[PDB]
Image (tube, rainbow, N blue to C red; front, top):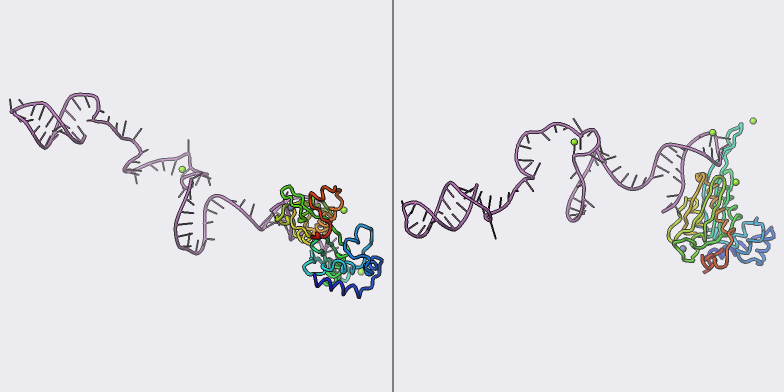
Length: 229
RNA sequence: AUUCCGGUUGAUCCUGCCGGAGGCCACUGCUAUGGGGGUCCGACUAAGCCAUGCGAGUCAAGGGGGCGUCCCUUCUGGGACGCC
Ligand SMILES: [Mg+2]
Ligand SMILES: [Mg+2]
Ligand SMILES: [Mg+2]
Ligand SMILES: [Mg+2]
Ligand SMILES: [Zn+2]
């Protein structure tokens, strides 16, 4: 944590904002990550996340989900292009997913990491399993669903210490968001990695669309964003 | 662990089947130091055919006999005892 404080301080001083939200962050009128959500702002400068969530630059908080090469046909042969699917998170409450293209692998990786920061979202965590009622944010608070392409994903709460009972892509994405235990069910073509990742991402996002009462927050130990001990 | 991964195109998304990865049972290649426990070993084809030995006896306190050893007298005998 000590490295990232000074890293954010270094980034803040030499950064020239170009947008309104960047100006708000630069002048110190916005000081917390949670204050840029749920008000319709547009996020176009990656430095905002670097200042407010510096730990997404750690090597352990980034994941290269997949790499593919695609071909365009021309009378002078085949033109090759790289597509990279990547994800980032702070392992507490925030996660982002991105896609980048480039003529060579390094450019595509850089752009994919860059776009993941701009698509960052915050989720809700809790414990809602029938056989584990512990009020601790180690799983999803209730059953959620998502879909993309032909892939349908359903996430079910699990007991503490169970593990992530899901394919590897889902494992990585859920780990980056700070979830330890879950059950799952799927339909469709999971071997299409992009759609699988997007479906898991949408299922995580849909935790904000479920109406809840103040009693439920106490009952399931629902936490929004950072756990904040 | 309420799970996926490879395969149809110059490249993409689907439907759909094949293969991989797990457990148990029967036969089998190569190779093997020790102990304990258990309801394991000619069932699948032939409920096909069988040399040899064994796998159902017991009762002397139900009854007349045979044989043997002893005691009493014994010509003769009567007892007791033990086998058949
Ligand atoms: Mg031409
Ligand atoms: Mg759609
Ligand atoms: Mg075809
Ligand atoms: Mg026979
Ligand atoms: Zn729990």
